[PDB]
Length: 291
Image (cartoon, rainbow, N blue to C red; front, side, top):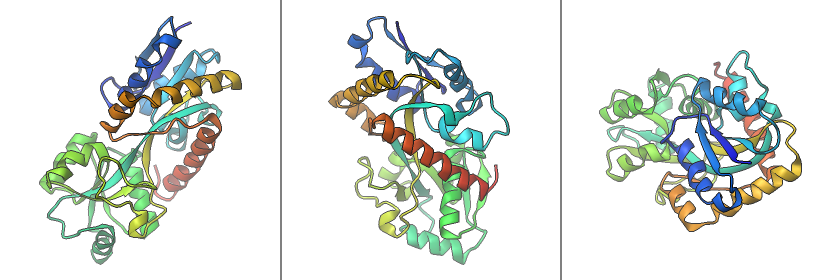
């Protein structure tokens, strides 16, 4: 019985790399092999649906960022499955979002940026990867927490947005840390804040938003494993224990750090609470801003 893990995003990105690094460590346990299948489309809904439908024996699993687990059903009018019915296994890792600005912007930190945005109401421009994306929703969270108003400029993905931020065609981007990190290290962008409960290992000198007085401003790309509805608890538990064991291995922790990723390996109970908490949080953000 081979373990099939569907990643509903292309090969070669973070969503693909993390479950692959982990699955490399699981080989001895899964003699019939561990197979990562990439199935792109519809915000992860295409791959997600294939797992949702599969036999709930724990040998078909979805390894995904949040979209098809906790977010999409708040964005998409109708979908082929109900995300609230996923059986949680684990969270492999978290990659925090950050507030990044063009260095000519005359702000040094979050409070200064907040003040700039309020003195220049409706004028500061933020890029995103498109409506409903993590960058769009993170910006929306920030604005609802701070009562700032900023102009949305949607891009086809991260690279066009990052190019415009570097060039100065937009003022700000709520990027994932690994995208912006090397630009910040070369002083070519300025990361003001990390939207997480603790600082990032990859950027020890940049404070969190909590430490800059905005403690509710947490926004991370979490990579979870979930099983089809009705997968038995004992199988779920055995799988999570296996994933947690791999995340211990130094080589896995190093390859995760290389992506800006903090390993988690949370137990099924913790994982479920977190997902349910995230669904609620992001629905609340989407309603206050629209889809």
